[PDB]
Length: 49
Length: 43
Image (cartoon, rainbow over all chains, first blue to last red; front, side):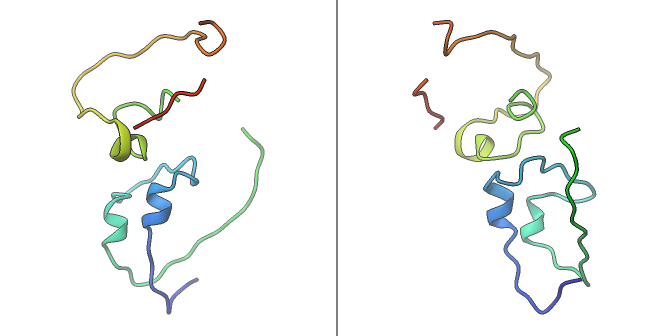
């Protein structure tokens, strides 16, 4: 969980470093606009397939 | 980078360089060109 921050989804939205940036439910543009109650994120690593 | 350069465009290709609007279109074919003809750039 994260809070107590200020976000900038911009550098991730444009800097394509995030390769397979495929998303749902939202506009990965309007991501740098909308605000949320709270966030959660899981991370991991897997094979290339 | 077919999926990259395509409708459903998003990325520096789109904003920076090149993304024509969404109109019903076809696609491009496969070949060798760096070593079948390099230093060539986007916009």
